[PDB]
Image (cartoon, rainbow, N blue to C red):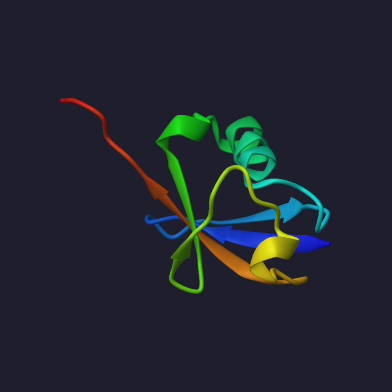
Amino acid sequence: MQIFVKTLTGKTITLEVEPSDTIENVKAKIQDKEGIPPDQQRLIFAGKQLEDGRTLSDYNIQKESTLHLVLRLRGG
């Protein structure tokens, strides 16, 4: 199934995923497309932060759903 990720600057990315895929796997696909490391990425769906050890089906994410990406800043 296809899903959409929106960034804080106005960008929408389209990803091909399976319901059994883990959040850590979704972050790895974003790193491949945009070069953002998984430790600096935060994913939000319906106001809830998604955990790396859970899957897309655990949060009831369905086809054409929109997730939000937030970037963290450690030091500096």
